[PDB]
């Protein structure tokens, strides 16, 4: 499964945020428009996409920009059906319970911001922005969207920017 | 002085009643294992209650 | 089953209340915060947890305290689905009927206060605080929580602090 | 024999006097009422028995208290028939001669106060309170009771509180 | 070697400092007089030695007391010959270099205060009082004595009381 998830993430145009030769994060295109975590500095690893001017959203520490329709051709597919269970992402699985996403300890660190969370159908259900040490596991700070289109950001108390 | 003493007794009784009401309100405000009790504070609003 | 219940209770950080070398009760962490029966005197068998200041609740004879998030990592999972049937706890099974928990006679005594009641999934459904002789069985005084979050304490008439 | 003596002492409710986790003595129940050496500080190792209020007797450095009849059910059996010979107690045998109890050297020390002396029938004949170095043996300071009910305390000159 | 070191430490009268049933440190007798780290609370595990009144030395956080000559019969042998190399102590070996004692990381923790350091001849060369995390190793705070009889305490910067 993880192999297929990585293949889908690579085939879909996704590009890390390079700064001085260091990967400081990741950015992806979902719903035909690029999003980028505002706290991560640098430029997208795509000259064509870098030409797009982004808008800032301080409240969520996220940025967004318009993507040309011809490049909107193949982007991430979002869904609002988020039942309890387990999902998959770049660094393995993620447990969803009580409305929160949690992963085993030692998974995720500074520079992983921007990795989306995929369901069994390969649809995006959340975007990982950070995390905080949670003993045997760690809880990720993510943003998710309900069927009504409301943006909700779940941030654990004293969450670290990962 | 009689009026002042009566007023003081009234204030003390009101304070005691408020303290007992706060204790009664905190009774459901115990651990109640969820670590989350917004709704009891939002409904009862006894004092220092739901932020939202 | 009882083996798995004991293994889950031991793996999850649970500590008896020691006083002068005598086990006078038990305390556990559910939902990421420690609870302790107020009538039981002594200190938790954990120096790190003992550092936490508790708050009193005379109405239910219970205490509570905040647990650090890093230690909140692995605590008991509570559920509100409490159908009639049988559940499991440290000293065997418990019968749930008419909204009351009952166990066979000779099970439970002074010093068992604090033992939780687990379902088939290992989720906590009630906390045992005491009991009273009920002939061929004994009825335990427990606290349970509905899906609305209301704390309800069921106490048999003339129940003894066990 | 010593095995049976220890089994009888354990089956009968006997409890050492614990202070700060250290065994400073022993106390037992004979004739349905608890006795305790006054010079030994601490509380009996039984919460139910600890609830009993004791009375002091400075003359013999002993304390006594009333035991509930239901707990008087099984206590030590005393006898006044104390012929010369050998008896048994926790740390082996004891020689009775000239009205005095003596044991081999190296047997008994500080913290053994309260150990009774049993006959061949398991009946108590004396209570050990102390002792004094007597060369190849040591002489114990004990209290014994005649058939007339007179309390007589035999204390060697310069006896040490053991 | 470690076996012989433990045998020598046990045969020589050494007693941990017990408080509420917990080992909070260790104390030993060297040169015929007892020493105890002042920061460690509790009483020596020896009633006869506990009868000795100690004197305080705040500067080194150490205590000392006079031991009866008959008990001075068998104490630790101190030497001033402290060449560079490796020595042995309760938790294995210790490296001596640049006038400082160092041991591999994970060796030593709160409650080990009082353990002496022995040479190949079983003679004491230093007393371990604390330590501080030093990466792959840890540096112990110790006191040593030169051939002129000068007490010198080596304490790493920000050393923790272990």
Image (spheres, coloured by chain):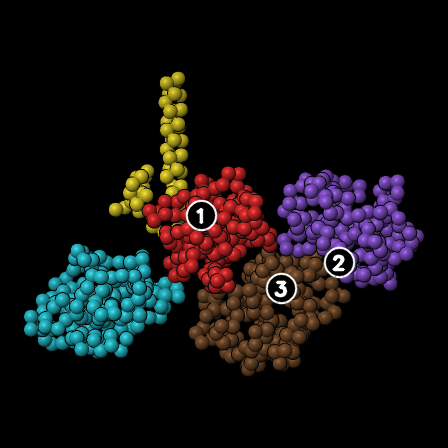
Chain colours: A cyan, B yellow, C red, D purple, E brown
Residue at 50 percent of width and 63 percent of height: C3
- Mark 1 vs mark 2: tell me if same chain: no
Name which quarter of the figure residue A150 lies in. bottom left
- Residue E21 screen position, x and y as percent: 60, 58
Residue that carries the numbered disc 2 in the rendered image: D6
Residue C97 marker: 1
| Left or right: A99 in relation to C18 | left
Residue D46 versus residue E94 in the image, above or below:
above
Label 3: how many Cα within 10 Å (few below 14, some 14–19, many 20+):
many
State the residue at coordinates (69%, 44%).
D71
How much space separates mark 1 and mark 3, taking CA atoms? Answer: 55 Å
Q: Determine which quarter of the picture holds residue D109.
A: bottom right
Question: Looking at the picture, does residue D143 appear above or below residue C72?
Answer: above
Chain letter behind tag 2: D
In the rendered view of the protein, which quadrant contains the N terminus of chain E?
bottom right
Tag 2 and tag 3 share a subunit: no
Label 2 SS: helix
The residue that mark 3 highlights is E16
Q: Is residue E129 visible?
A: yes
């Amino acid at each position: 499964k993880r192999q297929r998830m990585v293949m889908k993430l690579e085939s879909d145009k996704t590009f890390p945020i390079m700064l001085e030769g260091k990967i400081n994060g990741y950015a992806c295109v979902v719903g035909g428009k690029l999003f980028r975590p505002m706290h991560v500095e640098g430029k997208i690893d795509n000259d064509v996409l870098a030409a797009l001017k982004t808008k800032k959203a301080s409240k969520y520490d996220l940025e967004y920009a318009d993507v040309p329709q011809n490049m909107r051709a193949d982007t991430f597919k979002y869904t609002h059906e988020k039942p309890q269970g387990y999902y998959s992402w770049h660094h393995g699985a993620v447990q969803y319970e009580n409305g929160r996403f949690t992963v085993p300890k030692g998974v995720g660190a500074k520079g992983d911001s921007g990795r989306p969370i995929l369901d069994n159908q390969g649809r995006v259900v959340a975007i990982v922005l950070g995390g905080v040490n949670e003993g045997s596991r760690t809880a990720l700070s993510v943003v998710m969207w309900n069927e009504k289109g409301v943006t909700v950001k779940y941030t654990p108390e004293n969450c670290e920017q990962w | 002085s009689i009026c002042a003493a009566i007023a003081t007794v009234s204030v003390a009784a009101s304070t005691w009643l408020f303290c007992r009401s706060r204790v009664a309100c905190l009774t459901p405000y115990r651990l109640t294992p969820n670590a989350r009790i917004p709704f009891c504070l939002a409904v009862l609003c006894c004092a220092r209650t739901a932020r939202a």
